[PDB]
Length: 258
Ligand SMILES: *c1ccc([N+](=O)[O-])cc1C(=O)Nc1ccccc1
Ligand SMILES: CCCCCCCCC(=O)O
Image (cartoon, rainbow, N blue to C red; front, side):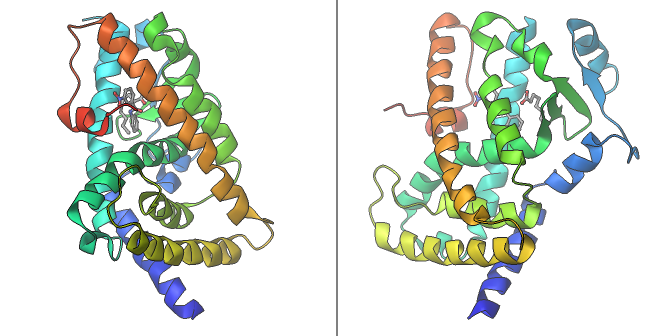
């Protein structure tokens, strides 16, 4: 019944608003800088980076540590949103942990896209804005840590998804079932099947003239996979480049190579 699917869509949206403080609707309002109830401070050079302390170790390193702390926050929020996904908390515990461990990064970049345009990315809850170029011009083991994310975002943001869309889509991502090592795949897939039905009907109703958006959205899951693998291997470079650099354990746990 389509009415049951709309109610799951409503449920996940509601829970998405409660778990993610910076929605895409907010992010866009801040970025489309004429709804200026509060506009961001813009970091485009090392000069503004210091003035950013006045409003909102090595430069690229502590840029990287701040990006790192934010990932911990995002994982926390994603973990909270997952629990609201019906059936998720009744799966085997080891699989719950496995679904998060692999799903978290794919979600982080889906939602990072909402904070991006071609020119840069919102930071500090939308109080700041770092330009693509300032990042791209960081020192070589850090200069390229965000460019593929910018590349994905512009492609992803062209589908014009709104938060109610994304809520269902990031639920589809967690409840995958092809994650390495799942003890009990079939109940995952029954959940995901219901999420996909939810997503299908949501995309149809919310975007009636956007042909095969559903398919175009699922296809985007290959772009996400590649970005994650690109990311983990640049992380292991930096681990050997600076054996004095430290990585949050919640992030370490998620990072098991191979
Ligand atoms: C940036 C650098 C390093 C990591 N990491 O060690 O996992 C993560 C990030 C990153 O993408 N942070 C982030 C997540 C969500 C929103 C803004 C920034
Ligand atoms: C939404 C808060 C983001 C603050 C993290 C600062 C660096 C973020 C990044 O470069 O991706």
